[PDB]
Amino acid sequence: SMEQVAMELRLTELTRLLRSVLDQLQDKDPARIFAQPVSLKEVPDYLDHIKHPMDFATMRKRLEAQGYKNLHEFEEDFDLIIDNCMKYNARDTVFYRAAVRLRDQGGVVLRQARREVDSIG
Image 1 (tube, rainbow, N blue to C red):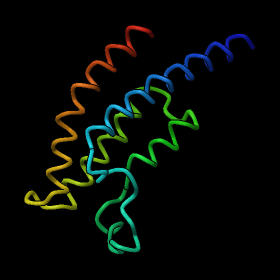
Image 2 (cartoon, one colour):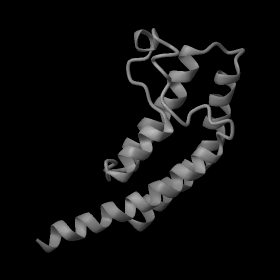
Image 3 (tube, rainbow, N blue to C red):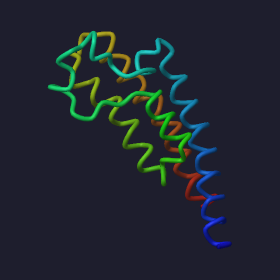
């Protein structure tokens, strides 16, 4: 149908906007702490602690499969990256501190993304 196509064009454009958002968020992680999944070879007990692991490469795979239907779903995944880290790692670690800085700096980006998503529809 023509409607299914119009819907698919909207999703494609949301994917375009979320790709830009993702790039801007990942720039706030210059140490690349959150770039890839925590290695289960190097942290074998990880899934005993963290039940829903997340990282930027995993988000990128979902994004490019047009797997985010709305900004809320994308934000859920970003928040997992941060929240998983702040639980597994102690306050006095470079990992915890990296997550706090990502959260703080990301907030600004995500605030305007929400306005853009609502605005453009």
